[PDB]
Image (cartoon, coloured by chain):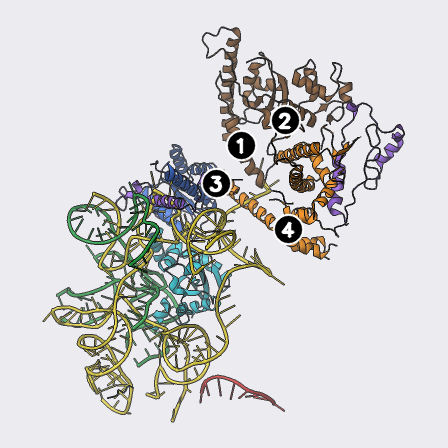
Chain colours: A blue, B cyan, C orange, D purple, E brown, F yellow, G green, H red
Amino acid sequence: KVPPTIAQFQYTLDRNTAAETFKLFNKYRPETAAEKKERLTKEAAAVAEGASPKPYAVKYGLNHVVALIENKKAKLVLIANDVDPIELVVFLPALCKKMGVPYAIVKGKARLGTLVNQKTSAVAALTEVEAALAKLVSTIDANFADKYDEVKKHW
Amino acid sequence: GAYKYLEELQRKKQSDVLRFLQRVRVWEYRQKNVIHRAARPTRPDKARRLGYKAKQGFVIYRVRVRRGRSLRATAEERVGRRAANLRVLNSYWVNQDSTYKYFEVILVDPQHKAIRRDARYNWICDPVHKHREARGLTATGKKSRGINKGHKLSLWRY
Amino acid sequence: FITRSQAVRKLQVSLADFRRLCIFKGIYPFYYAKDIQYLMHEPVLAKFREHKTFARKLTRALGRGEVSSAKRLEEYTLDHIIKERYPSFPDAIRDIDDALNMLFLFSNLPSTNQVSSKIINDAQKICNQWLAYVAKERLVRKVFVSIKGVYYQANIKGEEVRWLVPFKFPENIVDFRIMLTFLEFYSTLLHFVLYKLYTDSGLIYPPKLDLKKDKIISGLSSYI
Amino acid sequence: PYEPLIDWFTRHEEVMPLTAVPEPKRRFVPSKNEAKRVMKIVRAIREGRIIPPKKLKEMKEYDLWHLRAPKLPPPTNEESYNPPEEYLLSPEEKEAWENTEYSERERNFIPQKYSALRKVPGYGESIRERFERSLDLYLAPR
Amino acid sequence: FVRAESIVAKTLATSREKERIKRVSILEDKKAKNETQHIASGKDFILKDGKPALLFIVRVRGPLAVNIPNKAFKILSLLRLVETNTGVFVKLTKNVYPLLKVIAPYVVIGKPSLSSIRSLIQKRGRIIYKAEPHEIVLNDNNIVEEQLGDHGIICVEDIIHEIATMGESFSVCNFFLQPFKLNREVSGFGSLNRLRKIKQREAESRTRQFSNAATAPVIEVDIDSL
RNA sequence: GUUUGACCUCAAAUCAGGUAGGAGUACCCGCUGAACUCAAUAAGCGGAGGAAAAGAAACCAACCGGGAUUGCCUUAGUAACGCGAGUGAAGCGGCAAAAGCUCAAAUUUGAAAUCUGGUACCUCGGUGCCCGAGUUGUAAUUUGGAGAGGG
RNA sequence: GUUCUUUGUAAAGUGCCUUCGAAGAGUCGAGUUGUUUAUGCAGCUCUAAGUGGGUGGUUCCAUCUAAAGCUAA
RNA sequence: AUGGUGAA
């Protein structure tokens, strides 16, 4: 029988809210290798012949995502359920709850990574966004963090 | 980093979560062959602190050894025998059973150009390190040899 | 000799691509082994495999998302086959008599899901060059007005091509896939044949063309 | 065996971050690690081994001169739009030709006559004949 | 079952379409009265008049799935352009001029060419008549010589001349032509078709744009595209 | 939308790029180990090089501190044991040579900046292009002698 | 020595002011059972700490940071 | 005793 600390996944965000979260994340897809390379080539050509606002992108790497967490810099955290090493993500929801940061779980690590170029991403987070982020956070809260606040129970 | 938390989580092995994980993984390991390739290390923190890296050329193996010679050294030798072209740099525990013990072993390919082209691991390609586990030069082998620090006929011409 | 299924399995190429390969090369009885062996050495197999890999990678990109990757992924002619089947230009002219009927029929077909508009445009433009060349060397010798159409016979260096001009009336619409492959092969042949004929005629190729006249009649009254 | 967990620690929220690491200038500077690559590309362009992107578009640009005879089909046989009056066969023979079994059918056309050019009908069987000939064009044993 | 978002989107689109139609109709009613005292504009212009001019119109799909509105639906039914990718030639007139704005969002208009008209007529054509469900194509001129030709339109070339020269029999022939069902652009789905459709859709936004302004100039694009 | 692709896993190749068997074995590294305390000796097993191994202290030290590892003299036939046959060292001291160090470990996040393979040029490799590995972590910056951010 | 290149808001060190500031777990350890020249190793139940821990002798002191690795003489 | 040899 699964312990109460396990099975927190599998029970994940609903269809509509998950789709909305995916759509919101698609608005800040990080520049891919080809796009970054072509942009750098264009910049070099412009400078070689004849100073920009800070960029924004989704956070995906586990190490730096956790680094942003604990510092309270993570506005939202999205976690995959089918990750093979469960211990990598067992403590992440607990850390997010302790730090007071919204968090959510999704089914399919590959689908999580498809919005961040990489084949798989395990977890994802956002640092900056326009205004639908607050509504999405409220929906995620009311649908998973407060409705299923009894995750500590059952087996 | 996640490793800072993963190490502490793995420290409390008797905890419910790790107890469930071990009993879940024991059946999967048993269903596998005696020696089989592992796509990724089940204990990434341990492997990473053991000098293993995810770059190309690194291979993780797993092997089952009967319980009841040092088990770690026997497992290393067994994996090296099948993996003739690989070098058994180190191995570590992952799971134990009543009748069998499971130890994960990380292998480094010396023939791969990636391993030879970096100065941090090119030393392993030298012929001196061939069959390192056979001579017990690994961490388990050195410990078994008793290479501790401290207390723990000749005739000249005149 | 090996069976058709056996040859396909040896080539491990789906029947759809095997049809194209056979049409380009030509293999028939049950089939002689030597022909299959020669086909297996053709470079067209590598190009077909590359196209299949491109399609599967494009599908992967579309399923994953990031359409920019699919757009960036977008980055051939059977010249060798032409020499094999046509050892010399007179041989190509000889084979024209039956090959070009398909092209001339396609020149007047309507655009549909089975035929892209580009194919019809290319077929129509090829006529704009064929008729233009024939109207300069004055090789027309027959003008039989048949029910199937005006049976032209241009004395193309003494082979009397029997090409038929379909009527301008709507040709209401068989497996067009084979017809599509035949049209592609005939267009590839036509490119080089027209190049050679224009070079022989002494006119600089490609010559200038008038589009305002094309917007009036759209046909031979253009492209000098 | 079956008991719930206790959220003794996951009930209060920290205010200050766990660490007071100083803020690095790089976070406030435009990606010097990226200016390095920009200047590397500038050097490569200066050396001339890298083509500017415009030249790539500007450069996105010839006369090349079992093999039995195909046996071409016979030429036209009195299928003219204005054929001799004697060649306009009776309807009974035309009906038999139309009802004749396919493939085995000998004639590839139906006799007809039209005086006015504008009255000439458009051929509807042109595609079928071409499709039939396509089979022989590559399936013929030769 | 249908998800909520679709209904809300359809309602929002219908509201905007109805508001635009009402505003355009109200402005045109005052413009016709010639008061032209407290309206945005009174004159008409085209940028890229109500003078006679033969134009080709193509029924495009979109905008979003707005429920059929009475005014635009009836106007399309007059031209029987309900089906997508269908087009018909209409004689431009001052009375017909407001119809462009009335059904601008659903159709694209432009000035055709003699070669384009000839090719379209000789390549496509329908005669839905003698049970008379047959979609017989203009195979022969015998039908044109019998049913038509009372006014001298005996062959297809006569129909082409009437359409291009706006002859007396233009109304009769146009109705007889049973306007053609032009093939859609991509006409496919699957591995390559998805990407081709996505690439083509980008040009639609830059070409088929509606400013929604009451005094918006008539949208015109060259028919040479197809 | 019962169609689909991803991710994960399981198989196949007269596919491309790679490697282990065996021999020698004086020396070396581990397992096993017999008899006149004999002996952690001989034989047997597995693995390597010109040396092997060890090597930069959870060391020795009770001093006015030394300061990687290994060899020689000395310590010493002493400490210690079996006090009985026999076994039996080590610090310090002098001699020959001396070398340092690398990752886990704290955010590169204003840019996975990393690298294998295929291709076109000049070739113990370098450049452009393409793919793949990579986020379940590839480069620089830190290895306790601390170290990082800034002025 | 001879040379063609030297570079891009590129890299490093040092003293001053200031703020931050980690450590190899079925592992040490413990009991037993076999081996060892009363050290160590091995099988096995238990198996933890970080102003913490390992080795020693005097009323608790001296030194070091183990459970990863490379390195000619 | 070690490691091999063969046979009814």
Label 1 residue SS:
helix
Q: Which residue is mark 1?
A: E201
Q: Is residue E100 above or below residue D27?
A: above
The amino acid pointed to by label 4 is Val
Q: Marks 1 and 2, how far apart in space?
A: 29 Å
Q: Chain of mark 4?
A: C
Of circles 1 and 2, the one toward us is 2
The amino acid pointed to by label 1 is Arg
Q: Which residue is mark 4?
A: C13
Q: Quadrant of the C terminus of chain B?
A: bottom left
Q: Which residue is mark 3?
A: D56
Whether residue C56 sits left or right of residue C105 in the image: it is left
The answer to whether residue B125 shows anywhere in this view is yes
Q: Earlier in the sequence, mark 2 or mark 4?
A: 4
Q: Which residue is mark 2?
A: C214
Residue C75: x percent and y percent? Answer: 52, 43
Q: Are marks 3 and 2 in one subunit?
A: no
